[PDB]
Image (tube, rainbow over the protein chains, first blue to last red):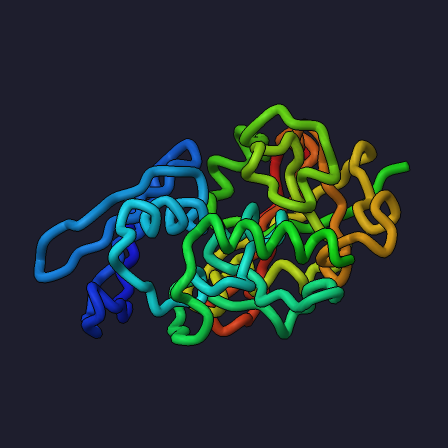
Length: 132
Length: 128
């Protein structure tokens, strides 16, 4: 299966439009590609698209991704990762378990709290998990 | 004691009724599963007691159609009971299946469209 999604990015300070390709193949293989100006800037291969996206953002350190999956407080639950191939995640809040109304699509638009690295996102998530 | 649980999944029932639900890694640590089941990949298949909790996942947040599978098993771990108030997504009513779910334990597959509408017909697994 191949799905495509246009996204907004900030490349070296400039607002730009890019296109993600999600290629889901047999044996849990998720391939996430990003195209910009018809050129493939990067690709990640993993078993879910949230992991793919974190790898992609680490490969492209000069780009801010204006997407929910790049937001500091967003992370999949085990269930959302497993059942949705990482496409559905949660916006998390200090001291609170995640609720259905907190669910998001990782490639929906977001421009707040996204100028952060995948490692900072993992750190926020670890501190959140400990806050419960 | 056996219980019915449900799982959203985009994979075909031809594949699932044949192979069942397999896990992605060997970690048996339920705490690590709840924190991040990709780091390390956990030896559990996630399911829920509540069929409605599968819909947003099966449809990728209303973007595509997918399936809700039903299964009957006796080896699952009730995540909320095991983790208590620490359960990070307790509203999901998660029963984590250690080692996955055999194909013979899967009852059927019911399609759901992107708008969240469950189809009328459930496709039953002939292995039952």
